[PDB]
Image 1 (cartoon, helix red, strand yellow):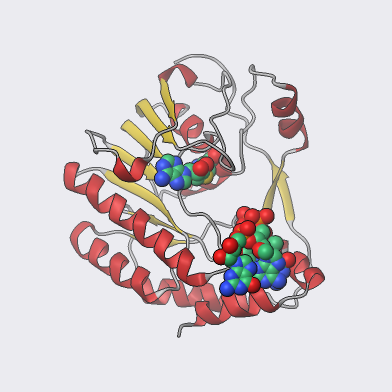
Image 2 (tube, protein in one colour):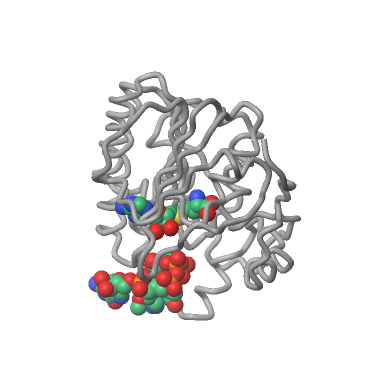
Length: 259
Ligand SMILES: [C]O[C]1[C](OP([O])(=O)O[C][C]2O[C](N3[C]=NC4=C3N=C([N])[N]C4=O)[C]([O])[C]2[O])[C]([C]OP([O])(=O)OP([O])(=O)OP([O])(=O)O[C][C]2O[C](N3=[C]N([C])C4=C3N=C([N])[N]C4=O)[C]([O])[C]2[O])O[C]1N1[C]=NC2=C1N=[C]N=C2[N]
Ligand SMILES: Nc1ncnc2c1ncn2[C@@H]1O[C@H](CSCC[C@H](N)C(=O)O)[C@@H](O)[C@H]1O
């Protein structure tokens, strides 16, 4: 058993009030009140982020932890926050975005956010059975939370296997992907094997809620994986009992128009 396993048990043991105070204490939160209503009313001419995912990828890029370029694939694009971020980047030439859609899942939001014309959205696509194709940058933000840590571990293992398949097709591609449950030993083993062949490392974005242990793997950073995970678990465990709220910041606005 790991510290993150204990974190997950302590999380599930929270009362409702305990859970909601813990969830958001100390985290960066974009201000989505304008964005939310524009999406709700169906405004397509907008550059405000279509989801909270945009600011997370923006943070990874601005830190230099990912370098989005060339032909980008977005595996599990959901509403498209990563696809629109990538399409607005001058070094990106095109985005192929894929998501399952269906009941309980987000379909792509269609807006004129800068570079939208460079995105080819395909909904109703399962990426886990899709044949990989050429890409310079491979992005994947898949990993659905579960109260069951073993399910979160297996969901995470499937994402890492997917990234191995896309690296097999594209050994030189940069990769960035969500690791939902890095605290699980089957996940650590798979991350080690990936890191040994492809390099890379783990990082926590300051926008992730304390109710998830998610971290992001990128081929462009480094770091011992176990220590990265353990630092994050201790930091998550140390926030239990904190009552401070979130730090609110402006939402990303990419502007509108074609590229
Ligand atoms: C009920 O549940 C709930 C839900 O879930 P889902 O997701 O829907 O899934 C379902 C599933 O799972 C499982 N389970 C459940 N339960 C149980 C189980 N298992 C066992 N073994 N046992 C038990 O008990 C099964 O398999 C089924 O089928 C959830 C909700 O969520 P949503 O809405 O979806 O959102 P998201 O995105 O996910 O986010 P969040 O919210 O933040 O979450 C994350 C995490 O956290 C936690 N939580 C949540 N919540 C809401 C809560 C919590 N915790 C606490 N303590 N409290 C509260 O309230 C978890 O871990 C998650 O993952 O959730 C759930 N829940 C509710 N409640 C509860 C829960 N869990 C645990 N515990 C509790 N108390
Ligand atoms: N097997 C699969 N094939 C395709 N899409 C999947 C999938 N499993 C999960 N997904 C989708 O992957 C998406 C992950 S959410 C990603 C958030 C996104 N990066 C943003 O910025 O908006 C979800 O919408 C989920 O429906």
